[PDB]
Image: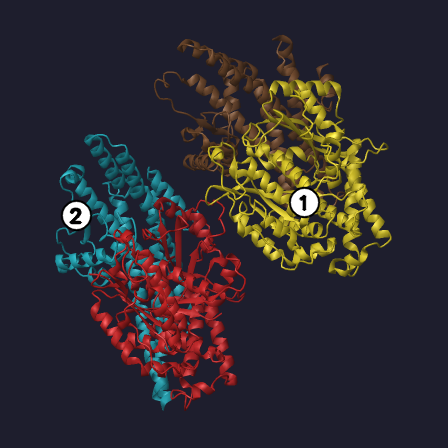
Chain colours: A brown, B yellow, C red, D cyan
Amino acid sequence: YFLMDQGDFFVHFMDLTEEELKKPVDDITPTRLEALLELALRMSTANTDPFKDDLKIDLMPHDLITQLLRVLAIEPTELTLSGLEAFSFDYVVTWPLSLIINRKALTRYQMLFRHMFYCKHVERQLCSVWISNKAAKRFSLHSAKWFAGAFTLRQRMLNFVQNIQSYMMFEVMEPTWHVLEQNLRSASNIDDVLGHHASFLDNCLKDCMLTNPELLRVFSKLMSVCVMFTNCLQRFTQSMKLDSPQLASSFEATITKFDKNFSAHLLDLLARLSIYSTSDCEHGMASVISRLDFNGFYTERLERLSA
Amino acid sequence: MPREIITLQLGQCGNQIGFEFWKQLCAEHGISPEGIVEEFATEGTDRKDVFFYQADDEHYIPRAVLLDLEPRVIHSILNSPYAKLYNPENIYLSEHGGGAGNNWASGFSQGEKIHEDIFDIIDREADGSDSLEGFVLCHSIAGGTGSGLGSYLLERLNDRYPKKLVQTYSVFPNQDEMSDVVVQPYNSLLTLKRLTQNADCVVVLDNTALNRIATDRLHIQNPSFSQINQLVSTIMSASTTTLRYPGYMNNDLIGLIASLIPTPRLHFLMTGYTPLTTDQSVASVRKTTVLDVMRRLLQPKNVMVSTGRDRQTNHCYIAILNIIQGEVDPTQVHKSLQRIRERKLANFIPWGPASIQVALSRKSPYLPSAHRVSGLMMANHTSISSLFESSCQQYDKLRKREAFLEQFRKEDIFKENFDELDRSREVVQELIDEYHAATRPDYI
Amino acid sequence: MPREIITLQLGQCGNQIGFEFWKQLCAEHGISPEGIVEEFATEGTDRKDVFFYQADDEHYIPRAVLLDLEPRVIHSILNSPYAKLYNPENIYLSEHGGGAGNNWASGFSQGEKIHEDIFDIIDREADGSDSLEGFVLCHSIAGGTGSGLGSYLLERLNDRYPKKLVQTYSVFPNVVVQPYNSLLTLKRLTQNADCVVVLDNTALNRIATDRLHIQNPSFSQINQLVSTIMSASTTTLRYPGYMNNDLIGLIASLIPTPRLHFLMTGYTPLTTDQSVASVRKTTVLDVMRRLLQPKNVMVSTGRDRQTNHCYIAILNIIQGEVDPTQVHKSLQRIRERKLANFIPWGPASIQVALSRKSPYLPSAHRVSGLMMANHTSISSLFESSCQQYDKLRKREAFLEQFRKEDIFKENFDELDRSREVVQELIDEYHAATRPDYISWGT
Amino acid sequence: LLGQGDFIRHLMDLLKPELVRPATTLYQHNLTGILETAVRATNAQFDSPEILKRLDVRLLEVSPGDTGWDVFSLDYHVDGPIATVFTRECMSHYLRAFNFLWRAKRVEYILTDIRKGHMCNARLLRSMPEFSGVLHHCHILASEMVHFIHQMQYYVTFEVLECSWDELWNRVQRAQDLDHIIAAHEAFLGTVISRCLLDSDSRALLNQLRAVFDQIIELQNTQDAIYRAALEELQRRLQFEEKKKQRAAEEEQEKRRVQEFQESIPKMCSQLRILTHFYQGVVQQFLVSLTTSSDESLRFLSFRLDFNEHYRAREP
């Protein structure tokens, strides 16, 4: 549920709550969210889990990025609120499992689930943008000059997001799960089990870069740039179908500006990761740079921006 | 939520491929030939609804419609062990067994004439699928029924489901062998045009390449159609392994389409499988390191597509997706990726986003795998344009000499003029030019 | 007090429909072909006094009278395994094997000639029934006995029991005098029948060919479908509950009143036993969508671009293990999506009744649902019948046999009145398509 | 609890000519005979014999201004272990739930009867369409009210009855003590009472449901009277036409009847429009009252009834 190990349930929840979570906080019915999640669990492979019904829809008290920044800076009328932003999984604990499961780990897991849901929504939006961008393939290739840049930017952003997501999923969260399993297998007492789980959680927190509100802001900026490009492409597709804000104002110039902003945010995140790798032996930033610069399209850009 | 795929079989070769795919799905899902679910496959955690629709006895019945213009393949499928596996209401057999006569125009006319029944079956499948993602059209570009009727069915599906992903299993004609159908080049051009204009993605399955792979790797002298059907079934199971096994990323066909097709025009992704060895060749527990798996996928001898190695144009892959089935260490996959990036084993598109994906998935528990780790490569590369150019050359050889043009002219599509064949040649040439630009820095 | 229903079977089609309905009732109550309750039917979930008569030896004798102008069908029924199930004293057959000669007037004359036996059987059934709700007349509108004798019996039942509902199982045609017989049967259903259930032969054949994959479907399949539909009509009477289990109430709910007696029938699932429906867990939403599919309608209504057909009233009898929350959700979703166009001149009549199937009947579908709806599309069939009647009348086609009858020996003013009534009914259903329909002329 | 079709279906079908009479004219023997005929015609005869022995017709105190429909109700007696499971409070809650369900069923049946009567006067008397502008104005509002009623009926079927039944069945499946069984039965009764607008703050909701049913009944009675009067006028016109066909006075009588119908159409249209306005106002007021309610079931019912903005385009 929280880590979306069962992909069928996560896909079903995304499909059912695409129009429900995307609605505002008071415009998205929490009962409707729960019903859509239940339908996702029933109509997905997660029904194979005996405790698949134990999961529920949860609403965060604040934005995930805002919470990450506030926690890092430790010692909602002006920010848009949406059910998609607040969508997450919740779990109840019953003693002595309630005496074992606490709310600090629960808060970390809920933050991870909300971040994963936002990333999945961004990837789905990029795929939808590229799918509607395929109309130029069936159309004349010489009447897509403005859309060529938009399609190229959508493909580049989707590929970068996919590579980053694959690297993160296989190196940050997966190491935490493996550490949890191995150390709990080596745990004999309550203290040993707590130490195992805490080692896994601390490895996850350290590898997820949950200490820089500037990094959270940069990731939010990149996601917003991708969303604006997708919105502009969707508006163009809707206008073309009928013919047959800032992003929607211009077709290619706005797409270029959004791509530039997203690339700047990604480069800032890469530089911060490289600095962390240089200071803390932390190979996660090097792996992220390699993943984004596999073909050297952005390897040269990152190297030049380092200077 | 299931991401349903409606398997459409067209022509004799298409019907054989569809029957093989249904048998492979039943075998992987522990479904008996009559459809009955095996006792060992009842408690699976795989998304069985995603890939197959169970029958009223919890019996995996593939949502496949077999359409053929001849009764021989239909009778063979209905007499096959998987006859009861498929639902009877989804199988349509044309009473007129005269076929298309190896003519794409005749096949298109037959598909248009049977559009009502085909459309009814497609609509029944769509209303019967809760979250249907799309339909897969398996047809042959060399035959008449497979080509024309495949194009007709694909156009009907594209019009009826614009929100559904469109994947086509197009059998390309043998570029090295003189096709027994003289109108084969025109039919291949028409099939290519239909795939380029109305299909979101077309996967080329070359029968000549399959025979070459069987002979060179399996030491199969003159492989039979049964061998080709079994290979197609194995390939379909490998392609649907990620859909069957709930993983961490790319759990839906929409995601697979997005990751496999960076260019809407150049959305054709070629397939490679490994290991490709005969059962007689017992390679002693050959430990496939992730680097070795990547090398095998990139190996031309493991590619099931005959793409011309033109030295004038430096072809490169627009995107690469590697699916490893079995117990694969993600650390091993990451080390292989790092070593491959260091060694430049594959040239990426210079005007395409950096796309190299590695997905970890588990193999089917009911299907015996001799290799603990298996690897399949799905990549969108400009090298397929060499095959498109070869098909265009064959079509031009038929069109310029008006060879086998009597069959096309006898149909309404080419009675007045050869605009259909000319459009087919133009679409193939346009795809080839777009692929050549994709190999060039000016693709973006 | 039991609530018995009297079954009147007229013509070959009517006799077949009645026999199939009796066989279905016997199977649902676990009654053998001889009418005796099976050992496994001692715990039957349906009280046989509701639909059948009980003999002194615990033998279930259905309260059906088979009237046929040809002895072949009577002999076939008496040679069938269900011969001992039916009481020999409740069936009257005319000794003169001349029939009606495919003439509505001759059929009416023959029915008047044999009125004594049919009327005596009806009187005996009514006196022997404690709470007889009404009679079900199953016949064909194009045949001779079913049309003429059916109209005569309907008029006699309306005159003797104006307070008793007259339900009819009219087999709608897909005979040169067929247009005249169809017009006469439609007029009789409109003027003397409280409800006429149209069974379109063309629609049944289309459904069978589309779903059963049976090349050149036989009349046996149509008869079996009619039997299944009639069993679904009485499925609402099997499960003790809240609402809508009276024959008159069912008439008022499916065919708004005796004036609006044209009601369409719908059955789901329409699939053979050999075709495995792909593990589609039958949801109330899916069942409603299947019933709402035009191909699942058992009435062949023309797709007229001039007339906007709409549903007047809908009564759905769902038999099986059904969760009321799911049923309510399906009804709500259909209303929200406007899946069914309700008559704008009347309240949206959407009723769903949860009923339990007979314990002795094996059901391939876990949940089944029968839809009886009064829809404006029945007027398409009425318009086709009126056009055929006008075409035959203008050329005096197949009028020689009618002229041979005393009713049409002098003139065809009765046929003119029937044609006028059919035109009035068509125009009334057209007004039903308009919101002004409630106070249309009213 | 009105869980199925047949039994109370036959009961109400017999009661249409029986239970419409005043409750003071209601007979215990007559109600018992109707119920026995319904049971023998339904599965209640084949139901549990203890249940059949406990199913009885219950009537309250006779007061002026009521009918036998609101008095006749089905009661399930509890004795021995059944008495220990259903106490006097349980019996009173069951009686209240049965009365509410009977009222809801009567409202739904009245709506269905009105719809059928309109759709059938569309067929019987549709000889002359000159009164086109009259029926639609009342028809649209009557359809809105009927949709509201159907939404309420689906809400009453599951938000109270189905939820309580599921809770009680699960509790009975997990019952290991008599105190646990008593608590489960009390919880099921309480859920039914709370969801079915039986509280002291929901007296407004019950009065609104009764008023919607009464307005539907009044509109149906007015429509039936108008249809009967128009059918009588049409019968007189048809008699004059038949006399003319068989053969100036007939022509003058027909002209006078046509003029009278044209003049009276405005009055019938005004009554229809008044009923339409009343039904629309009732629906809007019910939606407004439910909007301020804290119950999620009430909010969901209002949202379902206003998803298409049928009551929201009239009550902003």
* Residue A178 visible in this rendered orientation of the protein: yes
Residue type at numbered disc 2: Arg
The answer to which of A272 and B316 lies nearer the viewer is B316
Q: Residues within 10 Å of mark 1 (few under 14, many from 20)?
A: many
Q: Position of residue A54 (x, y in %)?
A: 40, 29
- Residue drawn at (49%, 69%), measured in percent from left and top? C174
The image quarter in which residue D272 lies:
bottom left
- Residue drawn at (49%, 60%), measured in percent from left and top? C208
**Can you identify the residue that label 1 sits on?**
B199
Give the position of the C terminus of chain B as an image quadrant. top right
The answer to which of D183 and B243 lies nearer the viewer is B243
Q: Relative to A163, is D179 on the left or the right?
A: left
**Residue at mark 1: chain:** B
The image quarter in which residue C180 lies:
bottom left
Work out whether C401 lies above or below A11: below
Q: Position of residue C387 (x, y in %)?
A: 50, 76
**Can you identify the residue that label 2 sits on?**
D54
